[PDB]
Length: 103
Image (cartoon, rainbow, N blue to C red; front, side, top):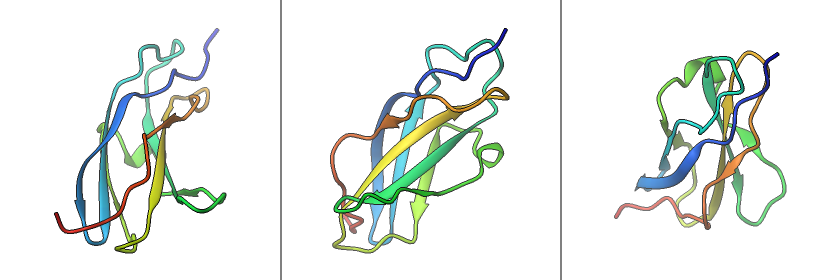
């Protein structure tokens, strides 16, 4: 008997550019009894209700991802799913709203 994994641990922004935001997280506390196969990153405009998927899970084995194609001076929010062969974790929201900016 196997379940979807738990939420990714400690998600954060760790870099930005004027057109991208880079997120990092840690492996979930539990994997539901089947190995983690990937992660799924979703991004929305902070002033929006429409989340957009940024990648295919099997394409994202590492616990970091650069979200590209973002508009400078526009605020975004992010959430990350852990995935295994059973399904998707509860998403782990990335705290706060974030601008893509040259820092």
